[PDB]
Amino acid sequence: IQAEEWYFGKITRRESERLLLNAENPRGTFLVRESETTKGAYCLSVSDFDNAKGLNVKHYKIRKLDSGGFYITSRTQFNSLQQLVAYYSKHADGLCHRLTTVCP
Amino acid sequence: SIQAEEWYFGKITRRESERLLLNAENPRGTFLVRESETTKGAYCLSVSDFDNAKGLNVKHYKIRKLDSGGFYITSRTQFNSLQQLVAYYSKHADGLCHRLTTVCP
């Protein structure tokens, strides 16, 4: 996974908001990094825009089932992280926006 | 002028540096210096490394600028230029994952 373009490893929540919040990035720009807060979990950080708050980043915890798979909600589970990224690029399913560009 | 240094890569992102450095053709210790995207005014030394478990990986060390003039990564040694910092760590790792060997192509 270290060689996945979208995996940024151990950056913090505040580093990921600085990397993403760029007023020249499309809505849905994202990255996957490790959760600082929950050992063993990952986190999908996604840039969003709404009228009021403007540009902001949403963070979604990704948990790993002990049998192996990954999930953000009870709707779908994925046998790998790349399957999760691939799925949410085509279907937002509760996320603020489908995933569009990897963080530059 | 640092703009023209072989090892200086300006404003490339954290992601681009890793894309440059994670490559089978690079020795452990391949590096580049760039601006930090996350801390303005700071630079960053990115270094390719290899460990048996994770294979090829990149480590990133922030380089802080003393307002008085120097540059540092640790309290052990400070430097008056980035050329000096790059030269020193090419001779001694001193906490880095590996001595700097190859300038990133």
Image: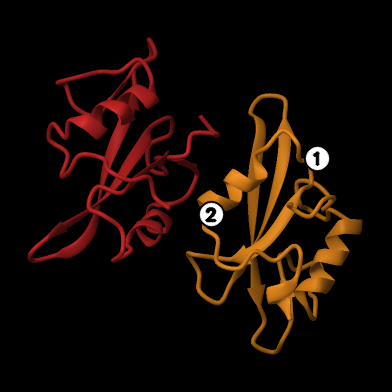
Chain colours: A red, B orange
Which numbered disc covers residue A21?
A: none
Q: Is residue A22 left or right of residue A6?
A: left
Three-letter code, disc 2: Arg
| Residue at the extreme bottom | B68
Report the Cα–Cα distance between label 2 and label 1: 20 Å
Q: Quadrant of the N terminus of chain B?
A: bottom right
Query: Can you identify the residue that label 2 sits on?
Result: B14
Circle 1 crowding by C-alpha within 10 Å: few under 14, some 14–19, many from 20: some
| Residue at the extreme right | B91
Residue at 72% in and 33% down: B24
Which numbered disc covers residue B27?
A: 1
Q: Position of residue A34 (x, y in %)?
A: 43, 39
| Residue at the extreme left | A51
Circle 2 crowding by C-alpha within 10 Å: few under 14, some 14–19, many from 20: many
For mark 1, give the secondary structure: loop
| Badge 2 and badge 1 both on one subunit | yes
Q: Are marks 2 and 1 in contact (CB under 8 Å)?
A: no
Q: Position of residue A45 (x, y in %)?
A: 31, 46
Q: Position of residue B103 (x, y in %)?
A: 78, 55
Subunit of mark 1?
Answer: B
Q: Where on the picture, by quarter, is residue B6?
A: bottom right
Q: Is residue A88 above or below residue A46?
A: above
Q: Is residue A90 above or below residue B90?
A: above
Residue at 73% in and 65% down: B74
Sequence-earlier tag: 2 or 1? 2
Residue at 55% in and 77% down: B41
Q: Position of residue B70 (x, y in %)?
A: 74, 81
Q: Is residue A68 left or right of residue B85?
A: left
Total number of numbered labels? Answer: 2
| Residue at the extreme top | A67
Q: Where on the picture, by quarter, is residue A71?
A: top left
For mark 2, give the secondary structure: helix
